[PDB]
Each structure stands twice: as structure tokens, then as C-alpha cells.
Length: 395
Length: 100
DNA sequence: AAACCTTCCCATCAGGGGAAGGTC
DNA sequence: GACCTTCCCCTGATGGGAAGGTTTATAAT
Image 1 (cartoon, chains in turn yellow, red, brown, orange):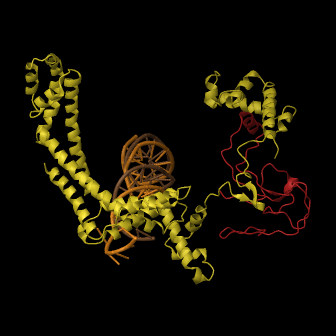
Image 2 (cartoon, rainbow over the protein chains, first blue to last red):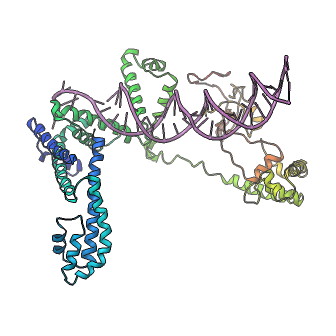
């Protein structure tokens, strides 16, 4: 075989199933890791995660000063790494370890004096934490180390947990296969819900993990279908409404004999009737432009589609002729009227202007302009000046 | 918006609409030829924009623009026959016109 | 599929004001 | 002449609602 679905179906066989002791003891390992974390918090998961991240932030703050002082005293001053670790281990609070390293009197010992100025203030940042967190710079590190160990325990146990029950995900996903969504998409969206179930399962309730994992995976597959199946995405609740309508119209088949009257579904369903026709008009799916056409020939639906945005040249020629005709006509009037018409309208100009807009730079404001236009249009209303343009209006 | 079968069509002459009923459907028995309108329909089109040269016409002759396009059942070009049957299928909830 | 809950966006309603009308 | 009540426009105040998210425990591979 070649397809990757086979590379997955036969790969998951290497991980053995777990029941029933396996469930409980791997869950106990998970809880033991998280319980290692719980004691480390001493010195709903939503706030718990912020607490964890705050400890991590404190350790990052300390490590920043660590690496800064290290780059300053090793890269910028050439002191050996051992001479830094030996003198820095134990205090990590005061400046007592810097003056001693100066008194060492090795060649690098002089460059410490210059970085002493730059390290003193970095140390004040590091020391202040003690007055905030009520701990020494070493206890922070130790607590973080132990809690990271707890995380590692939880991680190994949870990966094993999901790997063991992977098969149930396929067992659930094979039921839904044909909904415009490929198979591996279904099994993966189900694995996501399987993980979400693992992280939110109490092994102490005594129930079998199968049920909870089943619920979560079923939800994670159905909702995922609603999300990613149709090319035009539809609100999640609308897919539920469509499925309900289809279920009712399916059940009423043997009742009405052939099919139900549309007004009935509004009765059987909770919704008034005027929305049902919209819900049915919405469900139309796109047709591939490669769909074969009549005579079962090579012609396809992507061929018979014209372009209607384009304007036929028969009309563009008329547009140009009207351009020229109005150009010759406006020149027949006066210069004042010509400018007024080419201003109120966008003729031969950047943009159209309003009444006060035109009156602004014409030295006589609104009403004057209103009197010119109505006059010029009157002067052009007359035949023997409107024939060539009158040929353009046909209704 | 929903299209209309009304006989009121823009950009047409009276000689064309002479052959339609109040609802805009070709009269039974009246013989026609290519180009003639059998069923007058108007699809709503909007956001019309005009080259200032055309806005000038709108201002001069007072011939205002329409907010609807033209889709009509016109006789196929090249053939000229006689109407022998006219059928009208009206959806449910849509009010029945005169011809219907 | 249902079940109760939060973010965001409507296209409309209580409230204010700037004046406006009508009269013992 | 003022006073009491009346007739219309902006800030936003909001109930309304569509779109979105998280749970659901028999067991179910």
C-alpha cells in the first residue's frame, strides 16, 4: 500500500491498548505529576494556568539578570566560566562576590571594575524579587525545577493515554465519513476532542474513560464538519437547524405517504414558517465548473459562463461619440456656461462640484450658478441645438 | 430583490409593448417574430453610475435613469411563429396576477 | 442536539435640549 | 410678558440577536 491513511492505521498498532488497570494507573501518574506541581504552587484550571505562568514569569525575570551578568562578566571581560560559577553560587544576592573577584588580581580582574558599574544595577533588579515573592533567588529556581518535573510526568502519561485509545477515534469517525469532508480530517478533529477529554477527566469518578472520550470526540467531529465541510461556511447553529429540518422531513415520509407539506414543518418545528423557505433557499451548494455538460461531451459548466461585467464595444463606441458630441455642443455656449457645466458635472475634469463649490471660485455664489445652469440647459433644450444629442436618448 | 413580470419596461417603444397584457405576457394567438417580447420581465439593478457626459443628458432632457435592468422572453432571432399556448406557474405565497 | 453564557453589532427607543405655540 | 405644555433632532443606552464557544460521564477500540 501507498496512501498515508495506511501509514497511520498500521502505525497505531505499535501502541497497545489499555484496560482496565492501565487507565487507572496512568491517570494516577498524571495526577501525581500535577500533584507535584500543586505543592510547588504553595511557596478551575483557568486561574491555575495564570498561577503557573506567573511562576514561569518570575523564573524568566531571574534568568534574564543571570544571562546579562554572565555575558557582561565572561564575554565582555574574559573571566573563566568556573571562576564565575564558583563565586556566584551561594550569594546571587549581594555584590560581595564581585569585589572578591576583583581582588583575585588575574589579568581579567581589571575588566571587572568596568562591568561592576553595569552589574550593580542589574543586581538590584534581581534582589528586589526577594522582597516581592518572600523567597531567596535559589528557592525560585528549585521550585520551578520540581514543577517542570511534574509537567514532564503529566506529558508522558497523557501522550500514552491518547495513543492507547486512538482506535476509538476511528471507531467514531467511520460513522460520519460522507459529509463533504475527507476521512483523515474527521479522525484528526476527533483526536483533538480526545485530547480535550484526557485533560478534563477525573479517574476517580469510577466511570470508564470510553464514555467521556466518546462524547468529546463526537462533538469535535460533528462541529468540525459544520465548520469545514461547505465551501461557503455557515454559522454553527444553522447547520444544526438544517439537520433538524432534514430529520423531520425524513421521519414524516411514511406518515404523509410521499413527503410533508412545508407549512407542517413550521408546526412540527419550533420556528415560524417564513424562515423555513429561507433555510431551504440557503442550503444550495456550489457546482464544480468542471461538471460535464449535455451530450456527455468535453464541454463543462465552466465554459457556458459569460462575463457580464464587461461592456460590449457597441456601447463604448456610443460613449465616445457622446463624449465628442457634448464636447462640440458645450463649445457652442458661452465660456461662463461651459465652465459651469464642466464643473457641476465632471466633464473633462477631475471631479464634479456642488453649488457652493462652483460658486466659490466663480466670484458669484450659489444662486447665480443656479441661474446659469437652468439657463444653459434651457439654451440647449431648444431643438436645432439638441438634435445630435437627442439621438442619444432612446426610451 | 425579487424580479417582476410587469409589462413596464425601460428602453422600449410602444410598438413592442402593444402585444402584451396588463401583466406583461404575450397574447394567445398573436403571431410574432424574432426580437418581439413574449414575457416582459425586469431584474432589479442598482448603483447606476454615469459618465458626466451622460449626467449632462440627464440634466438637459430630464430623462431620468431607471433602477431596473431588462430580462425578457424575446423570440429567438431567425424564427417567426405563432403563440399557441401560454402557461403560468406561480409559487406559493406569491400573489396571482391578472393573467394567472 | 441541546444547554446556558459571552463578544460584537444592529437598527431602533428613553432622555435632553433648543427653542415654539398658544392663552388666563 | 412669563408660564405650562408641545413639536422635532444628536449621544448613547440599550434590549434584541446572530455568531461563537464549552460540556455532556454507563459503556462504546
